């Protein structure tokens, strides 16, 4: 009845959570088939996945653009070929798409800069470990953060490196920063996978108590951001919401020719020591309501 | 297949949430029938309800003993007769029962005490408005509180009254306290219904900015504790969880002759300005996962 293609820039616990949220919302609509592919952080594979979804003539395309520039031509094709395109989370560099949904990455950066400036009482040295440079969240996470800390002449960005969203490059790059900078008061990590990597670099150099750690994503579950705050590894992290259900509702509104917003902006919030506990109690319950919905879906058919 | 009778002491938004969770959890077991009654805060009516559940031969009894003494023989009776009894939230005076489930009312009390002492920097006058004196949560919430504030020589409890769990008495009692006490630094309310009562008495006397208000329950939804924090009426409230799902799973474990603990202590946490936002984000997401279950359950 309706087939949807999800072209996803990568695969990890954040994507996993969004995917499952989409599929879970699918079963509330009669007919709809959702197919999902990961690009494993590679622009070619993501083209291949988009071309694949175009060959299969899917009714709608959901994509998160790995890097902005290289993927622009490829999304434009799907658009001129008449297929409706939903951009999630990451953006492209033109307006040739049907609808955008995501959280404001610039404002998150701004929030990160303000939180650090407040915590360091207006004075200190920050190092930044970014996501993949050409992706729109890494760009904006940096811009917003620079905008915020410009208002504090004694908060200084003294080093920056591209960690490609991952813990591996984060560790090496943080090693280089520690070696070259005796005074570091804060690490700004673009996600909660970069963050533990930098921390482990600091831990191992006997210097993790000299600085605060800030990340983005704030997922519940083992190995994720919330847990890192509760474990006193991260001082703060910002909710980067997956909202898989609202993504599918958008798809359905478009397909079923219901009205829709062309742009849906989602909110963030800071998560830290003061609020990590109540958040965990609540997400723990969410997990339970989820497996209830999965048990209840299995009993149908 | 199995019949469970639930003898609730009260009816209100807190009880209703637990009642809904219990019913929703029962949909997941085959042939489990749950009948829920409210005593309307009356011991005789609650005695009747248990007696009724006994007469129709329920397989298990869930009870929140309105007051502890009046309800002990009745519970002791249903137990010796061989019906398993689950005590929820409130307790009776003796140990003769199958299992208890609730949160730690004493430690909630202690947390309130610590929170007020910290917020007032170890100096100030507190008024306390208790739940129904003869109920165990009210005894325990007061006693935990005394334990905490005993460690601060400059914190005084200057007045105390039995607000009987409700806004009405709370508002009259606060009113009196305000007239006799020119300096009040904090109000300790035993629940999120007593608190807005105390608050309105203060607001109407032009004094709400002089003190902090601390409550218990911290429920989501219009007119409850989370909203009161969000709206800056309540400075803090503590989570007193309902977890009707856990309550019914405990019933099923006993009836299915599966292993179960006699004592189940559930989690509390403080809710205030610093966490109310992520709190409400999560509950708002929880609330629609419920509508997503009413839909699915209502397609079977
Ligand atoms: O789009 C940026 C987002 O991508 C992720 O790496 C998920 O793959 C997140 O950690 C980050 O917030
Ligand atoms: O058992 C004490 C609890 O009972 C209630 O009054 C609801 O009936 C709550 O407000 C309070 O926390
Ligand atoms: K600066
Ligand atoms: K640290
Ligand atoms: K106040």
Image: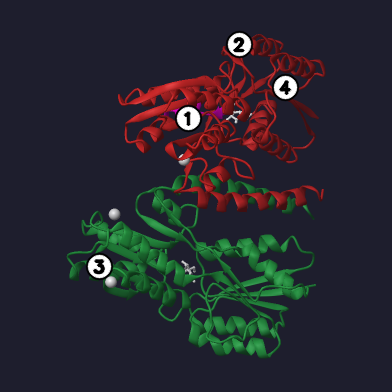
Chain colours: A green, B red
Q: Nearer the viewer, mark 3 or mark 1?
A: 1
Q: Does residue A150 lie above or below B99 as drawn? A: below
Distance in Å between CA atoms under marks 1 and 2:
25 Å
Q: Which residue is mark 1?
A: B188
The disc, 2 or 4, on the residue closer to the chain's N-terminal end is 4
Q: Position of residue B10 (x, y in %)?
A: 68, 26
Give me the chain letter of mark 1: B
In this view, A203 is above or below A104: above
Q: Secondary structure at mark 2?
A: helix
Q: Which stretch did the figure color magenta?
A: B102-110
The chain letter under disc 2 is: B
Q: Mark 3 falls within which chain?
A: A
Q: Quadrant of residue A263?
A: bottom right
**CA–CA distance in space, label 1 to label 4:** 27 Å
Picture quarter containing residue B29?
Answer: top right
Q: Nearer the viewer, mark 3 or mark 2?
A: 2
A137, above or below B125, in the image: below
- Residue at image x 78%, y 73%? A256
Mark 3 and mark 1 on one chain: no
> Badge 4: few (under 14), some or many (20 or more) residues near its Cα, within 10 Å?
many
Badge 4 is on which residue?
A: B39
Question: Where does ligand 2 appear, by image quarter?
Answer: top right
Residue A73 appears in which quarter of the rendering? bottom right
Residue annotated with mark 3: A175
Foreground mark, 1 or 2?
1
Q: Nearer the viewer, mark 3 or mark 4?
A: 4
Judging from the image, mark 4 belongs to the subunit labelled B
């Amino acid at each position: 009845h309706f087939r949807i293609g999800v072209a996803q820039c990568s695969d990890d616990s954040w994507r996993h959570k969004m995917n499952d949220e989409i599929l879970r919302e699918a079963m509330f609509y009669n007919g709809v088939s959702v197919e999902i592919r990961s690009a494993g952080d590679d622009n070619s594979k993501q083209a291949e996945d988009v071309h694949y979804f175009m060959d299969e003539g899917v009714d709608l395309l959901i994509i998160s653009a790995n890097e902005a520039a290289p993927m622009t031509p490829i999304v434009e094709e799907a658009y001129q070929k008449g297929i409706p395109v939903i951009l999630v989370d990451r953006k492209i560099l033109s307006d040739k798409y049907t609808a955008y949904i995501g959280a404001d990455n610039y404002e998150i950066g701004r929030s990160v800069g303000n939180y650090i400036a407040s915590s360091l009482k207006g004075k200190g040295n920050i190092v930044e470990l970014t996501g993949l440079s050409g992706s729109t969240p890494a760009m904006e996470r940096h811009q917003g953060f620079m905008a915020a800390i410009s208002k504090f002449p004694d908060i200084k960005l003294i080093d920056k490196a591209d960690a490609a969203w991952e813990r591996g490059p984060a560790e090496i790059e943080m090693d280089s920063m520690l070696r070259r900078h005796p005074k570091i008061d804060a690490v700004y990590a673009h996600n909660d996978r970069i963050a533990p990597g930098a921390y482990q670099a600091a831990k191992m150099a006997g210097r993790e108590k000299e600085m605060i750690f800030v990340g983005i994503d704030a997922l519940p579950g083992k190995g994720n951001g919330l847990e890192l705050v509760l474990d006193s590894v991260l001082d703060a992290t910002f909710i980067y919401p997956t909202n898989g259900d609202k993504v599918l509702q958008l798809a359905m509104d478009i397909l079923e020719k219901k009205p829709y917003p062309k742009e849906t902006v989602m909110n963030t919030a800071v998560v830290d020591r003061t609020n990590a506990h109540v958040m965990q109690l609540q997400t723990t319950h969410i997990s339970e309501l989820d497996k209830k919905i999965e048990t209840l879906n299995g009993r149908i058919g």
